[PDB]
Image (spheres, coloured by chain):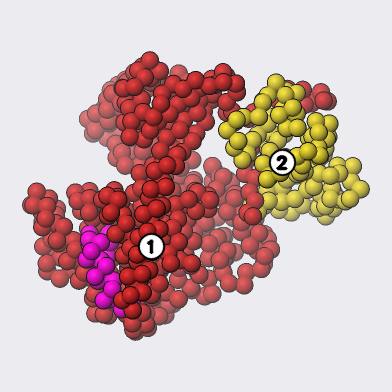
Chain colours: A yellow, B red
Amino acid sequence: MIDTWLAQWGLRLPSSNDATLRLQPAEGPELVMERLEGGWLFVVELGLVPSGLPLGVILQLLQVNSPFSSLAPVKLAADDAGRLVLWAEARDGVDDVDALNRLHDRLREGHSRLVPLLE
Amino acid sequence: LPESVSDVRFSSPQGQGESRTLTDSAGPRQITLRQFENGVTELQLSRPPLTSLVLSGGGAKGAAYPGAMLALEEKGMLDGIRSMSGSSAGGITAALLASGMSPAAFKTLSDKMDLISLLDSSNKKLKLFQHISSGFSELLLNVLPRIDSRAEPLERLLRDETRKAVLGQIATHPEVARQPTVAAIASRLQSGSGVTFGDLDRLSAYIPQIKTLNITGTAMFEGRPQLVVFNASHTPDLEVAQAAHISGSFPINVPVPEMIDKNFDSGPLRRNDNLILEFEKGWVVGVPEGLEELREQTVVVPPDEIKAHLQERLQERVGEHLEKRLQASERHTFASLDEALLALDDSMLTSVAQQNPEITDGAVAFRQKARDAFTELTVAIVSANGLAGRLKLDEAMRSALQRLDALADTPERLAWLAAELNHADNVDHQQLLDAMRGQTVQSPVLAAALAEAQRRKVAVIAENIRKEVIFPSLYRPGQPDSNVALLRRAEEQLRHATSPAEINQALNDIVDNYSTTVEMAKAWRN
């Protein structure tokens, strides 16, 4: 449950059910939470896709999406404006606190491994 | 939780715990302020004044339009409209309404005006395309003099009706009519000249019934749509009848956002609302107005009996939209009360102060001192007779700036003061900023104002690049999806650019990956 997950940090789900919430841990990337009708979309931003990436880097990025990736179920995508992002979907009534922390952990792990490759 | 995710806070302000209401529906904007246990302040207020009418497209389908104007008049909201904007054929209607025609007069004209015949007749205004053989928007303007469309029935009609409406408004306001600038305009019109965008701008300041006019169209040139904009800033001396005629003659619908203007401001409140009339999931994560916001401001438009019917329907639909917007509200969340108060304009602050002076005393004192200091600065600038020289500024200017500096005791107040010093219409502050551009200065407020002025300069350049380089290629028919993606990314880079370097990177990415676009990109880069 999202409110309980937030309670871990002494936070509470704001009563003004706004469509987008942003969390900033002391270390690591900002976590963007977007409300889906029946769940949440967890996203971490990696900046606009740079021009001129070497093939090996392109491969590493695309390999994040392997069904057997260690970052599973996180996915690497680009938004409509060309911003590289890692995302995962939290589904109400299925993903408990441990499941949510696991998504957050994988999003962070992916972020740390990839940011250096995007000079 | 692992070490790295031990502490976490909301990166944007979020109310926590219970809130208390500091002010309840204060003044005309119904300002409500709620503050939470962590100091976060939520501002709730009515929608901003409906000052803009936007007519997306036109032509035969515009038969219903008179119903919208009748609805605005019925609700006493037509005088509140300050500007009229129309795309393609919508410019025809916008020009008539902007000139001051009454809803009744406009209905009569619209009903016995055959827009299909008038438009079809337009005897080949493709001479424009040919003359542009020897950016684009400026080339089009430079070729109009060697084109003669003044006698075309549609243009003659628009010129005559707009002139009659303007002269009638002037005549009903004798105090205005006798003012020299107005008398000059009237004399020029009586001699046969047509109403210009500049005439409308000057008269609208005197007569609420006359509105400023914006006409935008997309002109296909070499398979690429070019955005053509006519208004008081770009084409003050162009007759509105000719602009509406040209815009209506282009063969690629102008996106509504291209008709809604960008406004730099010292706070987050929307300055005004639009009533957008049109006929008939995107995913951007952004950094760490939307179509949905535009949708809230849009009303979809639906043989004498049919005209009456379609107009009746639109009048009913617009009337309901106008009632419903009164029930809507705008909401903003701030990290502190003072920042919420800084978001309020002077009139709003006064309204809140009249109900709950205990929460506004500090903000009212700050506002009064800032206004007095800004005046002192203006007096110093104008009284200096030149801001150049071996020595930087003078004692009077320094003194005014020192007073502003003392008010900048928080990052929020510094930012507000710097944005206030950047108001584009303040000729004197603008002379000060221009005079000190690129220089190190002692005043923290002036330094912040200079940095903001530079950021605004970059944003303006980025917007021009978007319109001249990106828009035409982005909306080119048949543009492969890969190029569209590249262009969308460039638009994102341009929206966020704060330095010439960031603009250059956007241009380089297009040159290196796009498969005349590349030419225009290299042109802007140097």
Comparing A75 with B70, the one in front is B70
Residue A53, position in %: x, y?
77, 52
Q: In the figure, B129 relative to A11: above or below?
A: below
Dominant secondary structure, magenta: helix
Residue that appears at 36% across and 38% down: B423
Residue B169, position in %: x, y?
16, 57
Q: Chain of mark 2?
A: A
Mark 2 residue element: strand
Mark 1 residue element: helix
Total tally of numbered discs in the picture: 2
Residue B287, position in %: x, y?
62, 41
Stretch of the chain drawn in magenta: B96-115
Q: Chain of mark 1?
A: B
Residue at mark 1 to residue at mark 2: CA–CA distance: 39 Å
- Which residue was labeled with disc 1? B314
- Which residue was labeled with disc 2? A40
The residue most toward the right is A68
Does the stretch in magenta take in B100? yes
Residue that appears at 34% across and 72% down: B307
Q: Quadrant of residue A22?
A: top right
